[PDB]
Image (cartoon, coloured by chain):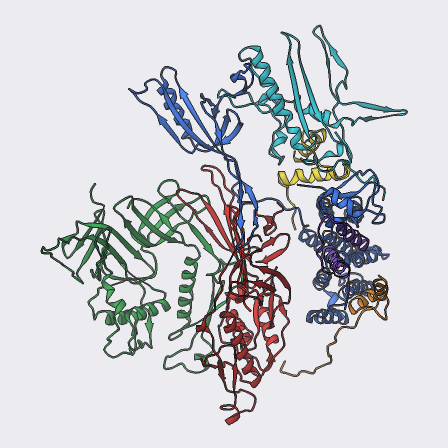
Chain colours: A orange, B purple, C yellow, D blue, E cyan, F red, G green
Amino acid sequence: FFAFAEQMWREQDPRYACCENLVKMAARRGVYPKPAQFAQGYVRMTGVP
Amino acid sequence: CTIQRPEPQALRDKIATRFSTNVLGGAEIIPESNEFYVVTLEYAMQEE
Amino acid sequence: CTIQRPEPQALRDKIATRFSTNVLGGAEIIPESNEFYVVTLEYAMQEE
Amino acid sequence: MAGPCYNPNEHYLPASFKGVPFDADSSDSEHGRNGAEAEFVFGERTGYADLGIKIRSYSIRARFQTNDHVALSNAFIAVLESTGPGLLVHPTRGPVMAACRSARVTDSKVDAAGVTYIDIDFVEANDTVTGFGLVGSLIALALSPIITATEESFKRYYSPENVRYYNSETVIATMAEAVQQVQTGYLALSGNDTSQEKWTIVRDFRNVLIDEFTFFDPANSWNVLRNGFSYLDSAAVGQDKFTILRNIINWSSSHSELDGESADAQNAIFSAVRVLATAYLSKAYMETVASTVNEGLAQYDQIAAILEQEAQIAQEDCHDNEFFLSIREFSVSVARVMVNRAYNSPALIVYSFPGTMHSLVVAWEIFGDAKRSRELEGRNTGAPWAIGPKVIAERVRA
Amino acid sequence: NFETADRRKRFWTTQVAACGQSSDDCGDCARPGLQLLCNGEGRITIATDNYVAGLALNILLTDASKADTGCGWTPGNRGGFWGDSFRSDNMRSGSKIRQVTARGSMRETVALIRAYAIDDLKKLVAYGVAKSVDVDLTYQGSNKIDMTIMIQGVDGNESRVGLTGERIANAWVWS
Amino acid sequence: MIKPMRIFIGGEELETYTSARLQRTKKQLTGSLTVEIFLNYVPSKPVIVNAVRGKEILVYVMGELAFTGEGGSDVTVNFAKGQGYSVTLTARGRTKYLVDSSHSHPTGSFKDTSDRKVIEALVKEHKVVLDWQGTEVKEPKITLRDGNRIFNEIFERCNQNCHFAYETRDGKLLVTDGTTGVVGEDIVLGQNILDFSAEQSEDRANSEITVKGHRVAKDVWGKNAIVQPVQSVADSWVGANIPLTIQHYGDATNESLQRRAKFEADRRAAESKSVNVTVFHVWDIGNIHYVEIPPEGIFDVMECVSLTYSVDAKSTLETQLELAP
Amino acid sequence: MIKPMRIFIGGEELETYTSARLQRTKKQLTGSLTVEIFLNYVPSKPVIVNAVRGKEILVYVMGELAFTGEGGSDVTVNFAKGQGYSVTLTARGRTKYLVDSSHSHPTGSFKDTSDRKVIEALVKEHKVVLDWQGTEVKEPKITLRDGNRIFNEIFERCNQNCHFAYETRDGKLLVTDGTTGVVGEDIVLGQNILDFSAEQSEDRANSEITVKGHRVAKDVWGKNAIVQPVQSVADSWVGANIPLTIQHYGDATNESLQRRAKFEADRRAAESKSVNVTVFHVWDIGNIHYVEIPPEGIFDVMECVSLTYSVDAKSTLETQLELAP
């Protein structure tokens, strides 16, 4: 019972919670993980009009 | 990693096995005996 | 876009649900009660 | 029977078929119920499954004794051979619709002259429509009509290329904000997703906002708004969407402060978004179990109010008559489902116990299985050891 | 929230002796109808008590569709109600107690009348308003004939557990 | 009882399905379905006719989705002088058109891409959402045969890389290299079995499989692209000598040679231990179950390969499996 | 009654045909027949055996010719310890040799002729009278495959030019591009039907069909003979997108592409609306009939595709039809 009470407290703290639970808490304060990015740039194309 | 609230049946059996092995020396739990009421009361306290 | 004259069955159900939800607070329309005749009279005036 | 005070003419109905009377002499029936008994292999236990009612059958025997019995008998047969089923007044089972399946007529000239017997074999026959099933559906909403209706209204007014030139910038800026709201909502719902589609969707959102000319076209503007909501709705299922949609509705309660036609081009964005958000919010409520009748109906009222407000705005000065009709029809459709869910999804009822009792004991007494106590947690307040003295539980439908 | 969660309301209900009783040399009869209730400053309102009793009156005092005869009826008085073609419960409204005909001795006719009365009020169980109904009819002379109808109701909140049957739906009228 | 099977067609429930049957097979590219419906006709009276040649069909088994057509692919109206007059229906997976449509690829030959980026450009001509979870492979050369069906090419390309190609229960296309890992029931003899039939056929096994195939890289030739690319893989479960040799249809690579060899090994191994079971009352294929048939001595984990739900007007419910280790 | 079905072999009537069955189909090159006979044997006494494996066979149905052999294409003598001892015959059309003979063409490659002038010089090695009524087509390049049967080549060539090839009731070979136009009967439900079992199917239809193929004429070779000759034809009755693509086996010409394309369309369309009717008592295939099945609302003209007369010694005298619109 002591372990259960402590464990279910640890799962509610940012520096000890599980990965899945961590994101759920973060979403409640406007913080989200950064998704992957795609490269970008400009290209010059020449041809007969 | 994650540990969550156990289900009823999976929880009652855990108590019965633990109670039987550490007290009655592996003896089976005969229904309607005094140990039967002790085991179920123990489970009730666990779930509440 | 176009809206046309509704069919009979699709028309009364609209009245019955509207009448039940707002007046009787979701209660079902038990046939042969007073509300049953109120609903059917309301539909008649609608179709004419 | 008991006692000598029987009057058979008083307890047996007079037989008939399709209106023609006839004299009955016997009465039988055959009821039942279809089963699927199965016995396993090497096992000491068996099983069973009930899969429907069995079609009935009736049999009657009729006697004719009056003079010219052949004419009556020979004229009653012409009624049995007629087409289609008809009403039958069984002597003991009362009126019921059947269809003759066979009939043997027995007669003689030397063995038995003057009496004609006829044995019949009826069958229950209930009329059925010819469309092989057109029953209505009452488990989901219809969003295609409202969405198309909203498209008609939005396209009608939002036209940034015709508004007065010193207001085009402001109108477009408002549209960019509206899309941004959907972008923020989606990113919040799928935080823990790592599929290969999340990257694509995020890139699509970024590209559209960066490009400037995309919103000069009414066709492009509508498509982005509609599609953006579609991704938002499918991001998560259930309670996860309540907060996200409520925030968007909050942002879309403003009204434009410009003048003339320019105001319409801006109110169109606000009105279109709010209606779309409300429709999707209703669908979200349909994916969760109603905790209580009172709570379930409170959720509905929160929706009808929003839809009613939009109807008044769209009919303030005949601004959009067709849109007003579409909104009104959608609201009644929503009510037909929301009310049904609250009152009939689990079919809750209030009990009256003689005092407080444990959750486990309450579950066993009502249903007969203590393992069902898990359901009582969400509906009744109070500690698990003090539930009562009035308990809200499910209907027993043995 | 407050335990008073059942939000279903109750509409008007026909009541016995609403418009008084009409007396005659043979006896005194009730004249049912709607009831008006008055406030201290006007503002009249309709009464809604005794739902099941009011519903029973509607069933008895309304002719149902007449059976085909082979000679026909005038279109005016074929019986029934045109609104019954929309309901989906597969039943027809009204009763048929008034369609009996003098057959055999008076004892047989009375027995048939009782049979129709049960066959009409049996619809009450089908709707779910009442869990049982039974009519007792006594013949004690040429003129004096009495009939009593018993309808069994239930309380709004379930109190008993382990019923052989089922809890009737539409029990929020508690009768 | 609470209906353990419900069906929808375009959102109007079927209340007269006098019989039903559902199938879901891992060794194919689309499921199936079949429903029998009672129909009536009154002479000299109107009849309403639907005759829907195409529309969605949904099947829910015990309050759970179990199929996603798209539907009404077939419509036949049986009829008899005696017994009765009825109708029948059929359906298949959302990718039905891939199974019966010739490809219309933009050009017809990739320059240099991966298998995933090819399957996306083939399927997405008909808007069928892909569900990819396998490992990506880089192919220097790909050129779809002109006019070949979508089913043939996907099956052909996914065979040499040990990709299973089969549908899910939602209306997607799932490409996987293993079991879904969803643990199922412990089907125990004397508890829930109703019938079974095991088997072990030696006519579909080979102890040693050999592969051959040339290379097609940008610049590879001579001994490094003709004779060099050969690889052998052996099962070692069969204790006999039954050699086999196969030819590779593609750009041979020493890693790809073994992957094709393994794919054949799994196919042959499964085909040599096919099982059938019937479990009476009516989650998914590819699951993991435990079995116990002491009479033949089955005590090994199994992966279900096919599933079937069948019903009848005379209450006869059943369900079948095609397990294999 | 006046014999509604009489048979003839070699001019001597068959008075002991204990059963019979005649079939004629428009989707093949020869009809068929099967007549069952009763035979006797007295032990230790003489017996006369015909066993003629070939002779003319004729079937007259209700005072009308219905099948021309040639006959006795097969003979078998069933036998049993119990029921009895009988003999079964069989026959086919006059083109029975074409369907089973490899061509012995003089040279094996035409220079420049028409299809008609090729069919004549191909089949006239077996003395089979042709019955031509279609449109002549001119081809620059024809080369019949070496050893290919007569059945394959005529069927192959006539498919590209959209010509139906089937036998008549007299012993000829009829190549036609349409119906005979002989208006028949009005098969109305409730008067003469016994079963209809109509059907529809989406698995044998395609909304867009495309064809391709190079050219062979002397003057055309290059860009105009490789990438130019491509044509597309669409059905427009199918409401979905089910593309198909075909290759042309011949000297492609834009007119010829559509002819082949439409031939596929007619074949696919027919396969999607097959009907099977039975009309009890016992003229020709390809006729035009009216039908009426209100239960599924058939109110459309129909063209018969197959015919079958079947009889038995007890409680069987029936006919079958296979319509299509």
Question: Is residue D355 positioned above or below F176 on the image?
Answer: above
Residue at 68% over, 21% down: E149
Question: Is residue F232 positioned above or below E170 on the image?
Answer: below
Task: Determine whether, in the image, residue D253 is placed left or right of residue G51.
Answer: right
As drawn, which residue projects farthest toward the top? E25
Towards the viewer: B25 or E2 = B25
Residue D130, horizontal then vertical, whole percent: 51, 42
Q: Quadrant of residue G142?
A: bottom left
Residue D285, horizontal then vertical, whole percent: 75, 52
Task: Determine whether, in the image, residue G187 is placed left or right of residue F252.
Answer: left
Task: Determine whether, in the image, residue G279 is placed left or right of residue G15.
Answer: right
Residue D9, horizontal then vertical, whole percent: 51, 17
Is residue D354 among what the camera can see?
A: yes
Residue at 43% over, 45% down: G293
Residue E109, horizontal then vertical, whole percent: 57, 14
Task: Determine whether, in the image, residue F296 is placed left or right of residue D273.
Answer: left
Quarter the C terminus of chain F occupies: bottom right
As drawn, which residue projects farthest toward the bottom? F222
Q: Quadrant of residue E93?
A: top right
Towards the viewer: B19 or G114 = B19
Quarter the N terminus of chain F occupies: top right
Q: Quadrant of residue E25?
A: top right
Towards the viewer: D336 or D191 = D191
